[PDB]
Length: 221
Image 1 (cartoon, rainbow, N blue to C red):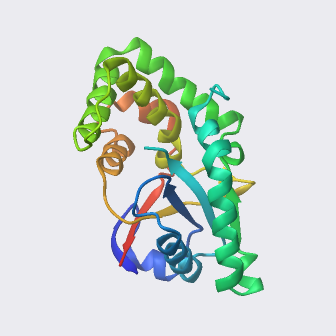
Image 2: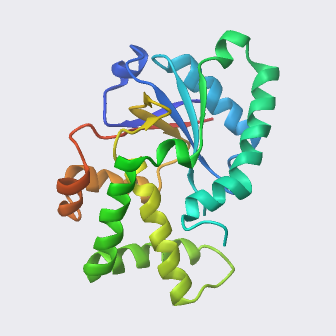
C-alpha cells in the first residue's frame, strides 16, 4: 500500500505530514473489503498530520436524503465492523486518532447549502443535468443490470449530495481534513479536478468552492 499519484499538493507536503486524511469508502464497491479498508487506515495513520477520518464517500424510503438512508441501513453496520477490526489491529493510542464520520457528522448547515445549490442547478440548467445524467449512464453501462431514465435521473441527484465533500475541505465532528485517500482515479475524481480548476461548469466553483480544494491521494497496493 503506497502513494501512487497526488492531486492538490506536492509529494513533500505529504511526507511533512501537513494534512489530516480522510478514508473515503465506496460502500458496496468490491475493492472496499475490511482488509483493504484496514490497510488504507494503516497508511493514513502513518502519513496523517494528526487524525484519520473514516467516512462513506458514495453508495453506487426512510429518509429524504439518500446518503442518510445508506448511512442508517448499511453505513452503521460497516462502521461497527471497521471499529472491531481496528481495536484488534491498532494500539489504544492509534485508535484515538480515528474519527468515524457519519453522513450527519459531515452534512451540516453549510454543507447542505452547497448540495442545495447543486440541486437547483440540476433543475434549472439542462446542460448540467444532462452531463450528470450521461455520467450515471456510463457507469451503468459497465454493469449487467439495466435502469430506466427516471432511475438514471434519481441516481444523478444522489451524486450531487456527495459532490461538495469531494470538492471542498469540510469538517467531520469539528475536524478539518484537507486530503482523502482513494485507491484509483475515477471519472468522478477527474470531474472534480476540472470543477476545482473552473474548467467545467465554472459557476459551481464560483458558488460553492473556496480556494482550499480537497487534496486527492491515490493509494493502492
